Image (tube, helix red, strand yellow):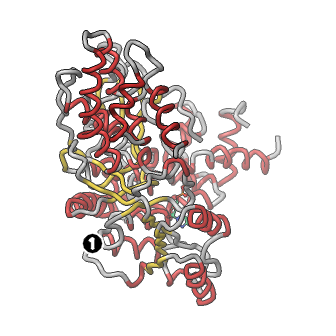
Amino acid sequence: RSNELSKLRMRFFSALNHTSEIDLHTLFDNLKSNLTLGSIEHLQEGSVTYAIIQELLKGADAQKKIESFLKGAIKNVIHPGVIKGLTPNEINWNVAKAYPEYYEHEKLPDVTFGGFKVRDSNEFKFKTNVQTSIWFSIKPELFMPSKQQEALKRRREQYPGCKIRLIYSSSLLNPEANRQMKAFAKKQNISLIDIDSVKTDSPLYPLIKAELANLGMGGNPAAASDLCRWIPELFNEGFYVDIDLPVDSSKIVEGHQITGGVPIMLNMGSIISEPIAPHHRRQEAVCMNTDIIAYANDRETQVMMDTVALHLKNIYDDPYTALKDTPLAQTAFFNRCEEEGKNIFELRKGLQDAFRSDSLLELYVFLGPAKFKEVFKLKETQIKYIDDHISEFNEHDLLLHLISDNPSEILDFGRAKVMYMDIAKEHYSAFYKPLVEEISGPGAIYNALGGASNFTTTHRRSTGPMLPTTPPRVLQVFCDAHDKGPFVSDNIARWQTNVRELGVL
Ligand SMILES: O=c1ccn([C@@H]2O[C@H](COP(=O)(O)OP(=O)(O)O)[C@@H](O)[C@H]2O)c(=O)[nH]1
């Protein structure tokens, strides 16, 4: 009646850059029976449609050619694209494929991701309104700390009526924490799944129960959480999101549906390296994280989840191969555990006990001479003499050898000991994290889906609108759940981040 037609016309003239090489009033008029606001976005500078229009304006008969092109582009590519949940990149590629006379472009390369060839058909569909999170409590009295409760209250009470599913373990909570779990879930209309009574043939189910039963004995609940994410009976649609992740309102799509070229998508970015030999060129390496994971409503989802599940099973069965390039692998303790066939729980627990002993002699047995050398910055001859004589040393004798040999580094024996133990503790995190990250975590998944060399290529930029014509672009356009979904993550690098300026905590 009509302030809506007026917003539409202003968006249109704005998108096409207020040009008068043609008559935007007539073009507008001739397109408006089939023009919606959602379509205009794919007409702006940066889009393939815009770039075609710029070349068509330099041509004779601009007005009519532009009109024909746009009627067609909107009707057959863009508008069915918007209705289906396609991104600007997916729509751009679809225009390029439809108008090869107007947009020169290469073929879709052959890229494998989890045993599956990435497609540009847009056939995998994913719900954004179905969200599953995992909270395994390490405190029997406490079902979930307040911060995670509020995060759940916020995603709901901001953004219904998405469905919210919460996996937990009853067996980790005392009866009172349990009753409080059920009431929290009921009050917040959360679908609750107890991991203790779930039915599945997955190999990952015993590993999950064991990580949880082994709490206090090297078991880790983030590692159990990680594994749950590859069990088809638990995840077969919607999203996995870290319980703590925020929703960006403006990113919610109105059909609550997005698409992909693989049936399981993840949070992805990439790192541009320093120049490498022999041509002094930068490499782009794709990185991926499991803080956000999307699962298509489709049989191909179960097949990709089973390839990944067989890789994780493998790692739990022999973790030494997975941890081979990590810092813990340089220690005497890891060597020994490897001979002895210790499992990941004893590896983790052994590591913990060593840094809880408050004993430099025990730290030495753990680290061994090479790693003890590097950690306390010793000269070769100094560690050689320590190692030769270690079976004669008490705790003070070792301490006296450190003091003579360095500081620098850190006149009272009690304080000097603390200074030296605290230097050793600086390395704890670097020793521990991979025992989750490279076992069930983002490092294991990365390898399960293809690893370092499936996902690294020579960095090539441009030109103009991004199309999926090299392997990292294929993955950027078609396989990344973070960009396409409504959750925010600063947990890994964004796409095409220089290794120098990383921006991560
Ligand atoms: O006590 C815990 C700790 C974590 N986790 C699981 O492991 C993930 C931990 O990742 P974290 O949130 O610590 O990474 P961040 O949010 O800091 O990026 C959580 O989402 C949970 O699913 C859990 O179940 N219980």
x 57%, y 59%: residue:
244
Residue 119: which quarter of the image? top left
Q: Is residue 321 above or below residue 309?
A: above
Q: Quadrant of the C terminus?
A: top right
- Left or right of residue 119, residue 163 in this image: right
Above or below, comparing residue 443 to residue 199 in the picture = above
Horizontal arrangement in the rendering, residue 59 relative to residue 271 (left or right): left
Picture coordinates of residue 15, whole percent (x, y): 45, 27
- Nearest the camera: 254 or 56? 56
Circle 1 SS class: loop
Q: Amino acid at mark 1?
A: Ser
Residue position for label 1: 202
Residue 284 appears at what percent x and percent y? 36, 28
The image position of residue 368, as x and y in percent, is 49, 47
Q: Count the marks: how many? A: 1
Q: Position of residue 396 (x, y in %)?
A: 70, 51
Tell me the residue at 39%/72% (across/down).
Answer: 208
